[PDB]
Image: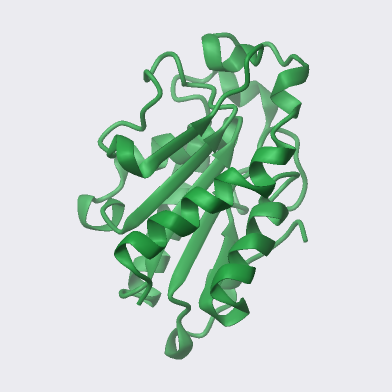
Length: 197
């Protein structure tokens, strides 16, 4: 439900084929927040419970609203935490296909982390979904150093954070349908395009 630590808790000897690392939005609970559980149950239906490990970004990522105003749209301590989980995934399960996602501050966190990631690990992230991406206009709908065909951004009309502002208006809170259908669909297509482990 809102906390999932399958990568940290998982046994190396029985690695999942797919590892999903997700960063929640500002002020959200657990380490998956409001959208992460919906994506997670749909990934589990497609790959089975032992086939996918879902891991939220917890630890130093406190999802403090004010950190949206920092240069990268989140704190450097939170980037170091997500970078460390991609590194843990690469070490603990070298043949697993990775997928990532984030909402709001967590989408800026996922973008910042993937930009700084070692190229050999970044290249294992088969697909990344970003909802209410706060750096959407500044980065022109892309994650730096990561291919457009592997990226899907969900930015609602009237969601002001997609258009260069940090005001939270009602469309920013309306990604529930996307997390239940097209965002898991995109992630499953991108994993099946390359395959699993």
